[PDB]
Image: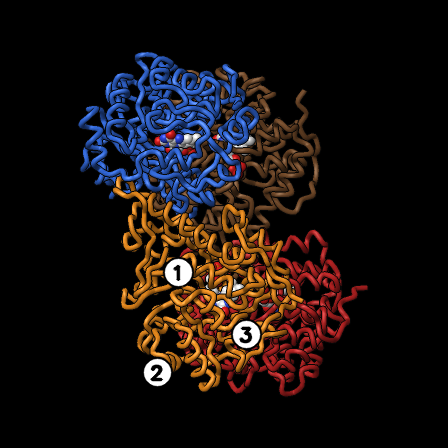
Chain colours: A orange, B red, C blue, D brown
Amino acid sequence: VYQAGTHEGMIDFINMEDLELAATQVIPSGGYGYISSGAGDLFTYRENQKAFNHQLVIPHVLKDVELPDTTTYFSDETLAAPIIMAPVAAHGLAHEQAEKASAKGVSEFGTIYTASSYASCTLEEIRAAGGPEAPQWFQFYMSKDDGINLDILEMAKRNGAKAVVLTADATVGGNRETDRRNGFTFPLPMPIVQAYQSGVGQTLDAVYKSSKQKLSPKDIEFITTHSELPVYVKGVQSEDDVYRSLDAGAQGIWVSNHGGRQLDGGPASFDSLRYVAEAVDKRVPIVFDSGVRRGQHIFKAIASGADLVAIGRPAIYGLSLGGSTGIKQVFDFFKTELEMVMQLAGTQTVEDIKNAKLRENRFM
Amino acid sequence: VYQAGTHEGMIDFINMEDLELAATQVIPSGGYGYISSGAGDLFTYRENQKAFNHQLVIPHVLKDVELPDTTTYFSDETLAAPIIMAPVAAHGLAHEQAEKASAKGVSEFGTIYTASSYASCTLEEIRAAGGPEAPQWFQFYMSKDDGINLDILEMAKRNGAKAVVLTADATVGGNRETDRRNGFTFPLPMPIVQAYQSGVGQTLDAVYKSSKQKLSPKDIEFITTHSELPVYVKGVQSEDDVYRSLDAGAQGIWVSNHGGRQLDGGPASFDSLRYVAEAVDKRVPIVFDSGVRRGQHIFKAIASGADLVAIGRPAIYGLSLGGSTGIKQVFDFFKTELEMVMQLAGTQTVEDIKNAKLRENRFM
Amino acid sequence: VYQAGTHEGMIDFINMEDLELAATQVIPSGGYGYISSGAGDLFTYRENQKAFNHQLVIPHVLKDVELPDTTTYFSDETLAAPIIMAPVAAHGLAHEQAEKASAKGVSEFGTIYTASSYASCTLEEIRAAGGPEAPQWFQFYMSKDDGINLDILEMAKRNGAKAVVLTADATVGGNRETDRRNGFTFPLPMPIVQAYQSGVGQTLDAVYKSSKQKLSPKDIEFITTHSELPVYVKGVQSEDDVYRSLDAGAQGIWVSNHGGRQLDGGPASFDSLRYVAEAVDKRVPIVFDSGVRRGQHIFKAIASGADLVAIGRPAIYGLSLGGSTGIKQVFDFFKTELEMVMQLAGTQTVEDIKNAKLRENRFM
Amino acid sequence: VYQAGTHEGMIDFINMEDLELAATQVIPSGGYGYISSGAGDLFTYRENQKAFNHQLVIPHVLKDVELPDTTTYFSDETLAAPIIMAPVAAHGLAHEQAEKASAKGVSEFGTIYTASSYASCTLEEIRAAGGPEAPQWFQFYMSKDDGINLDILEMAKRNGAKAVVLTADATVGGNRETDRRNGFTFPLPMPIVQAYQSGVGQTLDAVYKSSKQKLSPKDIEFITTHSELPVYVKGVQSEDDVYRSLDAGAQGIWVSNHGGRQLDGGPASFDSLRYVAEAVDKRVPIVFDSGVRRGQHIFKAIASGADLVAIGRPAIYGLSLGGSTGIKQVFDFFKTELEMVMQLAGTQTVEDIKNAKLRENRFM
Ligand SMILES: Cc1cc2c(cc1C)N(C[C@H](O)[C@H](O)[C@H](O)COP(=O)(O)O)c1[nH]c(=O)[nH]c(=O)c1N2
Ligand SMILES: Cc1cc2c(cc1C)N(C[C@H](O)[C@H](O)[C@H](O)COP(=O)(O)O)c1[nH]c(=O)[nH]c(=O)c1N2
Ligand SMILES: Cc1cc2c(cc1C)N(C[C@H](O)[C@H](O)[C@H](O)COP(=O)(O)O)c1[nH]c(=O)[nH]c(=O)c1N2
Ligand SMILES: Cc1cc2c(cc1C)N(C[C@H](O)[C@H](O)[C@H](O)COP(=O)(O)O)c1[nH]c(=O)[nH]c(=O)c1N2
């Protein structure tokens, strides 16, 4: 039987590196491999974290700043910080309480929770665990069947999703050789997608191949027609992808390379953010992820055109060790680091971060 | 007595790195040294594989792609994938069945087999092993004697060669210090070139020095006059070399640095491909090799102007461990990776790969 | 009880690297951690020392130079070399005689001593130890209370400070994870700031947070109004910061990133010096620090627009091992290396260093 | 008593790296330290060998080349190859037969021998050992005394020196910390400079400081007036140094950084060669050294504007292990590698090397 973390309470860590190492003591080796590794030779995965020092934050002086405020007004939401939970499959790999513990902790921190289509809990359980006022978005892995897609969108609406995130960069799985070496299969059901995917004993290759490969702009139009929720396209890393998305009626862009898990030999997401921000030209909101481990990474992404930054692996490691308490402590780590960076950079508010000018590193 | 691999059947590997390591268990150390190493301080050899991340593949989204097709129409041939067997000497160093096993396996995969002038089998055996419908090209190490050169061209014609590949970048051998340390000599005859080279007990320095050093455009004209087969010049890495080749009547260009085995301190072949593709301007087909270990490398070469990509060492390691079955499994590894890359890049067909735009890596 | 170094006399070292290692034998581990480490992942701290080879010194020939003279005329001062003591807190962490030993040694070398607001001695003791003719500057960590700030400025005047250095890049402490791992607290009082900070048993986070966070140009105007001493702004790394400082009446600019102790992910100070020197355009003097370990680093900073170069950690390591004798030996190491560099570069005097042209390193 | 190598005969090596290691078995540790190491943190010393791959040699094809000829016509000399012996002090540190063995071996190879002012033999012994037809140049470390300088120039003339090489980049010694750690002193006299320097028991700092520091263009004019031999200025790495040298009547330029032994933090000599070749514009001959370990390095230097390439440490390691036979084997190693590079690059003669175009490495 697969046994994940069970602790609910405060965890001891300094940074996200010793947290990642500590989680190896509570997550079974196959599950830890699935969470921790990446595609191919890991060039793109390693570049994600390195890329934040391609651009340098200037520690300005005499900026008349104290008690910097991370409070973020986004649509009709008031977030504690411009930091949100990325959609991550199967939280039962990390903690017995799974998405109930992660939705509760992210609700208590006070920010957006993005639910995965491949969750180990129902969306009804995720909504119940966060509470009725918790801001929640729905990440969509589409079926090949449009009847099933209508049913999943009506289900997202019933559960008060405020946006639909169409993940478009995992039409098939990457060459994840750690999962191959481990013979990884999912241990739990995937109730949200149960009409097309059973989860238990399935390879990640089989799971992604059960979803829709032939995604196109018509899929954005389908979601608009049948849900009337704003659509974010996730995995956007070029101008061409921005224009395809906006022309089809997308109301948000989510810059990502899937945490280096997909196409090895592609760019770091932070480098792609420059190209995407120029193409979007503030027409719609931008979410950014992949490689974020420090407050300075969040600051640099927002200065470079992101409106929100999403957290993946670090949140899952905190969940494994401390449940709702532990995942909230990870969000608090990022908020506390962002407050330090804001004071030393000279930015009183999140809007001031957007107006900061980074220096390109000519000696990387 | 020199004893190579003898197994015929399925081999267990994840990627080309663990395959290269596994082959050390079946190839005698001197033969393994000859296959695996490179010239001088190994700068050029190491740069070949690194250079593929000088250019970054964009994982596009909403591209309306599924079941990408690697089928390649080349002249009157239908290939399984745009992936061919490079000319590699003396397959008897790797497997007892030598070029019979490699020609059979490449025929069964369904692509072009390039026979080496320094083969351990006759071209008659290579044609018989592939079958009459197998696409085969003849790689020519020319004699100093034009009578011998006429005889070798008539022999290539009798065996249904569809092209002659004039290898022009090995007029002498490189400074291969692993072969020097090992006291390497060839253990088998070289029947195709037996009129000028006996093979058995000969150093690689002596073998290359027995062939023609003073290659010139007149040699292309000689091959056209006496065979009426299309001539590819192999080792082309600059505009000057393209113009010298085309002005002399070459009908193909093969971009290579001989797998880093020749002039240490020269460029990586993938970097040279940009210069050669601009000079050729689609006037003749381009074959590309040197350093290819992943589907993403094949995709990037084709996006950068290659029509076909040739495989060297990885195919020989598969041959050593599994014979015809093992070499076909290596071609299947590259085809399966290329299908994954095509889906995630958004390319339905091989012609779509040619139209993909890579992003230059400013932070290598 | 905290026990620091006690030796007064000559120390044995080759360079600043073996000196840093030797100091681990006499400084208690918590104090050594506080002195030696830096913020976050240590990118900025490591880049400081690497950055000196971003620009290359040309060893000119036939320059008609011998017995190069480091004598520096600065205001009405005559310095032995263009090399000064940086403000560093709590010298009692390094040596029992603390700032008495460091002020005496720097006075005997014959250069400017910058006293820290967080000193373990009174400014009266620092003035008494240096003697009445010793050039001393006062580094100011301001109170939130303007009455306390007036008292501290009157105290600096009574002790013959010739400049006030407003440190503006430590409004809060950086994420110094070595100090967190060690549970570091200060062992000694901070008498200069005793009206707002007690020092003993306090975290570095608490100490910086007791000083003023909301520094602005109004603070420069306050210091001018109440002391009539020239004001240097310390931590300046951009054109915007130069203009804010000069517009508010600053009479000096001190280029620094606080030895990599503050905002990780920011630039190396030597790289920032180019931007600051262009903005200042010789309107006021420039002091430079962060990463200086060799005479060639001092030469390059002066050629790039610095008038004076400040020494931090290396001086503290020398103090720990040899007291006044040991700190003077560190200044002598830098002067002797600078004389070697001046001879080989072809610069007779310090003004000749300013006119030297470095070559940018295109292959870093 | 200092005991150096004594063997006269053939030595076993593959490349200059295993030769450098083998010499540790026959050269006493202090002498080996003096020969092998460099200044400061060894940035410049390490960059010298790395810098050859800043520019890439194109292996051209169909160039109509065989049996490439390294024969070099230089003034009225006929050299075996465009490869000469650099001036290196005190060959008695390496072999008992000292400069007698090195002059004989370089004469038998058939190239220019540059005698050091700090030789362990007289120039009469060096001339006698090479024979009357051996091309020999005299490297001059000048006295502060012009009477002594006239005597040394008349001595060079009597011994048939064909050029005077004024070494201008060692007016003082670099910070050679291996020699400091070892307490190195010279074990033998320096007869050529005996009027001002005794050699025995002297530090390298004392030896360089006994020679002239205040070198200027007047020193070139002095040498022309009193010897009527062509003057080469050694250590030239910039346009300013070329113009100072030529304006003062220099008839040759020797590009060098003294093998990384002098000013750490300066450029690699191969990178400086581009700047110097553009300034010289073929007005006088150029000699190049520092970091040469491969035939490809010699080829690249000549393609980049050198007329001759000088060898230092590798020749001394060969001398230590095999005397005259061993030093000739090192010159033969470089000639044999240069012949391989010429064949693969497509250059029939040394003048053809000068016309080769390298590709700048954009991904170093
Ligand atoms: C274990 C695991 C599982 C998933 C993911 C990631 C990881 C680590 N990601 C990608 C995710 O949304 C995000 O892009 C990355 O996690 C960001 O990189 P970092 O983990 O922060 O480095 C992902 N994305 C998505 O849209 N749906 C999913 O179900 C999952 N599943
Ligand atoms: C053992 C071995 C032997 C040979 C070669 C290579 C190797 C590894 N190569 C070069 C070959 O065609 C090709 O250019 C490289 O193998 C490509 O680099 P990779 O091996 O794929 O990295 C080669 N080329 C050629 O034209 N004729 C030959 O006989 C040989 N022999
Ligand atoms: C232990 C310690 C303590 C302090 C400092 C540094 C160090 C190492 N620094 C920063 C200092 O003035 C200077 O900018 C750096 O020391 C320069 O970098 P290097 O130490 O030379 O590499 C510092 N700066 C300041 O203005 N007031 C202070 O009290 C201190 N305290
Ligand atoms: C042991 C030793 C001793 C000397 C030198 C070098 C070495 C290694 N060099 C510098 C020499 O001429 C040359 O510039 C370098 O040796 C070139 O670098 P490589 O040794 O080839 O890497 C040197 N140069 C010079 O003009 N007169 C000298 O007496 C000496 N002495």
Q: Residue at x 32, y 57 (%)?
A: A72
For residue A256, side relative to residue D135 (left or right): left
The chain holding disc 3 is A
Mark 3 secondary-structure assignment: loop
- The x, y position of residue C277, in whole percent, is 27, 38
| Most foreground residue, C98 or B201 | C98
Classed neighbour count for the residue bearing mark 1: other residues with Cα under 10 Å, few (<14), some (14–19), many (≥20): many
Question: Which of the two marks, 2 or 1, is nearer to us in this view?
Answer: 1
As shown in the figure, which amino acid type bears the numbered disc 2? Thr
Tell me if residue B340 comes above or below residue A14 in the rendering: below
Residue at the disc numbered 3? A190
State the residue at coordinates (38%, 65%): A133
What is the x, y in percent for residue D338? 55, 50
Q: Are marks 2 and 1 on the same chain?
A: yes
Instruction: Tell me the chain of label 1.
Output: A
Number of numbered markers: 3
Seen from the viewer's position, the closer of residues B290 and B88 is: B290
Residue marked by disc 1: A111
Measured as percent of width and height from the top left, residue D316 is found at 60, 35
Q: Amino acid at mark 3?
A: Met
The residue singled out by tag 2 in the image is A225
Looking at the image, do the residues carrying marks 2 and 1 touch, with CB atoms under 8 Å apart? no
Q: Residue at x 32, y 27 (%)?
A: C139
Q: Which of the 4 quarters of the picture holds residue C274?
A: top left
Confirm whether residue D161 shows in the render: no
Q: Chain of mark 2?
A: A
The residues tagged by marks 2 and 3 sit, at their Cα atoms, a distance apart of 26 Å
